[PDB]
Length: 391
Ligand code: NA
Ligand code: NA
Image 1 (cartoon, rainbow, N blue to C red):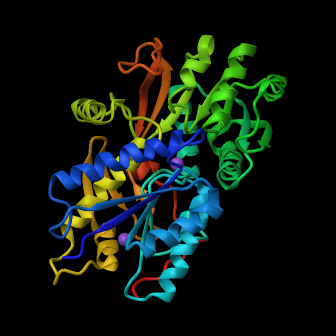
Image 2 (cartoon, protein in one colour; image 1 turned 180 degrees about the horizontal axis):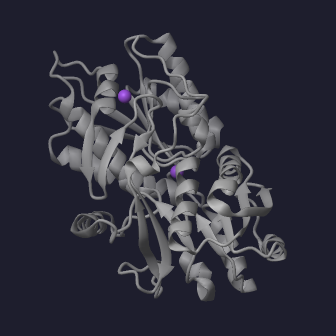
């Protein structure tokens, strides 16, 4: 029997690896569950890791290496810049290798194009995207009555941040805020966000929308704390470890929308949080839930692949993913065939002392206040989406 070989292409060492290492934790957790069950096709699934230290250029090299090593599946999620490269390299490889196609399981690169203009049959996205993140965070705040009329948008100047800004601007009229001012800044370079916080203060806003992550959110929060910023951030990634500690005195009341919260789905969500901590050493947050839940859907697909003569057929796996549905600790998870955007609930959460699971050893954690169903959460199929069917 051919074993299934899955390549994780991520930032896996060094000072920029905090997000990539959480992808590693989530991937090892869930592929670990599949392997505890026996793997796939009568063999353990092999997990081949490729430490990418070189951004998109590095990724192209690592994808070539992974495929040469026999990987039939590539997994990645920490950067949409990297994902843009991976998805195109996989698409082009597949055109040249009919019958030997490689799958790209995108567990967290959230830029719109991956299920829009760059959509293709062998890419699947298991995470939110900019539209899902920012519609849900704003609508949730509106439903709760904590969305003021004035907003600022601050994002990183690459595909992801541009998509967040465009989404926040596009939703302003219907949801009901004015984007008073907005900023795109250099990515992962700014060490002092004080001047940006000053600009936000000048705008006299109630909400600051941002898709920032890593230092671009950690240091932004720190600068906001030092300035005593009154506005609350409405985010996709505030529950990355470290942000609430950096928030210090201004921690209360900031907002995030994510696919998960330990208290959002009763005993099921909490049992998952506890099991994940038992295995990894920490409660799941930030990039981890989408990666786990996506790999749960993937595992369900694998169960539904028809027994063959021992060979692994990635087209059959792809069709099984399209057809699969699984009950995750947060509820139903499935895959939209048109664009390969996964359908799943979203939970909007506030930083509060009332949260059962605390963040960063503080008195505060993320407390859920609104859950949108899968139907309420998933974005419309993008106008730019076209997908070729087999084949
Ligand atoms: Na990600
Ligand atoms: Na369909």
